[PDB]
Amino acid sequence: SIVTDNLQCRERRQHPDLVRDCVEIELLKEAELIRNIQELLKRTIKQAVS
Amino acid sequence: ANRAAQHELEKDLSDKQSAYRIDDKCHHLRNTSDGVSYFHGVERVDATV
Amino acid sequence: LKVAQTRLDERTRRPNIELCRDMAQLRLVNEVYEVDDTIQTLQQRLRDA
Amino acid sequence: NLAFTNRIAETADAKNKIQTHLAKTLQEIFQTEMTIESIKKAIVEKSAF
Amino acid sequence: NLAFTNRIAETADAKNKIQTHLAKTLQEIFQTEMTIESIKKAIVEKSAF
Amino acid sequence: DPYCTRSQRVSESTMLPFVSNRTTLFTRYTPDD
Amino acid sequence: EDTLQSLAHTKATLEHDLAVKANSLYIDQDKCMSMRRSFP
Amino acid sequence: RGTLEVDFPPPLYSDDYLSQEGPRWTPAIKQATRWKYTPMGRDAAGQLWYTGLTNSDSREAWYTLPRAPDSPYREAYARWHGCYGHRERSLPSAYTQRLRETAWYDPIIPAQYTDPSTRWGSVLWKDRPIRGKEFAINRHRF
Amino acid sequence: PRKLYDVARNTGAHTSSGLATSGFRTAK
C-alpha cells in the first residue's frame, strides 16, 4: 500500500520534470518483489496445513 | 499542429480497434469450441499498467 | 475450465494503454478457482463412492 | 521506392513462413488429441483386466 | 402436513413479490416528488423574461 | 538569417518539446534484433 | 498433457506474430504506396 | 498399502511455483490539469489546461438541471461513467477496491466472508471403513 | 541527418524517448 501510494504521488509531477529516473526503477522493482514474496507465502502455508 | 493532433487521434483509434478484435474473439468464444486448451498459470500473472 | 483458461490468457497480448484490470479479469480468476475447488470436491466424492 | 520494394518483399516472406508453421502446428495438435484419447481407452481396458 | 408445506411456500412467494412492488413504488413516488419542483422553477424564470 | 527558421524547419527540429498527453515510453528496434 | 500445453503456447505465439506481420504488410503496401503511385 | 485403481482425469491444480516477472511502466491516473505547447512554429507558447474533471457540473440534480453553454461539462465521460457505475454497483466492494489505485486490497484473491470453506483450515474430517461401523459422509456440516 | 543521429542514439532495444520523427512526443 505504501509503494503504490508513492507511485501515484510521484507520478503526478509537473511537466519539465516528469522523467523516468533511478527512483522509478527501484520503486517498480520493489513492487514486483512484494508481489513475488506474497505469492510464495500462500504455497508455504498450504504445505503447512497438509 | 492540426495534422499532428490528427495523428494522435488515429493512433488511439488503432489501439482501440486491436482491443475490439481481441475482446470480441474472447466474448463470442463458446464451450465445445475448437480453439480451447489447457494453459496453466496465466491467472498467476497480472502485468497491467 | 478449458474454456475459462483460454478466455483468460488471450487477453494478454493486448495493446499498451488498453491493458486494463477490467472486472472481467477478476471475475475470470474467481471462476478458475471456483471450478478448481469443485473438481477437488467431486474427486473426493468419487473416492468415497 | 527501392527501399520500399525491398522491405515489402522481406516481410511478405516472413508472413508466408509463419502461415506454414501455423498450419503444421494445428495438425500436430489435432493428432496429439487423438493420441491422448487412445491412452485413456487403454488405461480403462487394463483396469478391467 | 404436505398441504400446509406447499401452501406456506406459495403464500410466502406472493408476499415477497408484494415486498418488491412496494419498494419500486416508493422509489417512483420519491422521483416524481423530485421532479415536481422544476416546473415551479421554470415558471419563475419565465416570469422574469 | 530569417528564412533559416521557418515552420517547416522547427516543425522538424527536436530540442523543442512539442509534447503530447501520453506518458508511455515506446521502444525502438534494430533490424538484426 | 505437458507436450499439449507446450504446443498450445507456441500456437498462440505464432498467431500473434501472424497478426502483426499482416498489419505491417497492409500499411507498407496499401496505404503508403498510393501516394508514390500518385506523385503530385 | 495395497493395489490401487485410478480412474479420474484431472490433476491437483496448484503445483510448480515459478519466479514470476512484473509489469513495466508506471500506472496511469487521471490528472486535473496538463500542459501543452501547441503551434510548431517560431510563434509558440506553452500553456496549461484544465482537464475537465475538476471544473465540472459533477452533481446532476434538480437544481442544476438547466445547464449552461459555457459550463465545463463533458458528455462522453458522463455517459461512460453512468454505465460504468451501473456496472460497478453489482460487484462487491472487496473486489471494487482492486479498481482503486493504492494497493489496500487483500493478498488473497477469494473473499473470506463469501467463501464457505475455511482459509487454511487444518482439519479435515476423514472416516475409515471398518466392518459394522457407519461411514459418515460430510462430517463438517452436521 | 541530425534527427537520424538523434534516433540512432536510442536505436537499440530499450525504452526510447518521445522522439517520433514527425509529430508529437511522449510526456515522460
Image: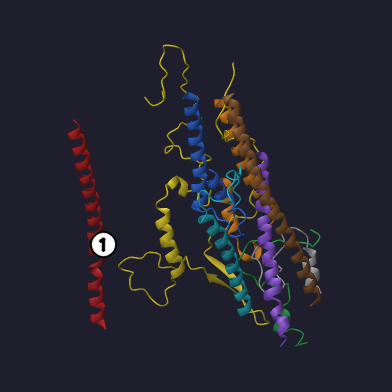
Chain colours: A orange, B cyan, C blue, D brown, E red, F green, G purple, H yellow
The residue lying toward the viewer, choosing from A37 and D41, is D41
Residue G30 locus on image (x, y percent)? 68, 74
Instruction: Identify whether C1 is placed above or below H46.
Output: above
Q: What kind of element bears circle 1? A: helix
Residue F25 locus on image (x, y percent)? 67, 61
Residue H2 locus on image (x, y percent)? 59, 16
Q: Chain of mark 1?
A: E
Q: Residues within 10 Å of mark 1 (few under 14, many from 20)?
A: few
Q: Quarter holding the C terminus of chain H?
A: top left
The reply to whether residue D33 is in sight is yes
* Relative side of H22 to C33, left or right: right
The residue at which mark 1 appears reads as E31
Q: Residue at x 54, y 26 (%)?
A: A49
Q: Residue at x 58, y 68 (%)?
A: B12
Instruction: Identify whether H66 is placed above or below D27.
Output: below
Q: Residue at x 62, y 74 (%)?
A: B7
* Relative side of E6 to D10, left or right: left
The part of the image, by quadrant, that contains residue D42 is top right
The reply to whether residue A33 is in sight is no
* Relative side of H94 to E45, left or right: right
The part of the image, by quadrant, that contains residue C17 is bottom right
Counting every numbered tag in the picture gives 1
* Relative side of A44 to D21, left or right: left
Residue H50 locus on image (x, y percent)? 51, 70
Q: Residue at x 47, y 16 (%)?
A: H129
Amino acid tagged 1: Gln
Q: Quarter holding the N terminus of chain H?
A: top right
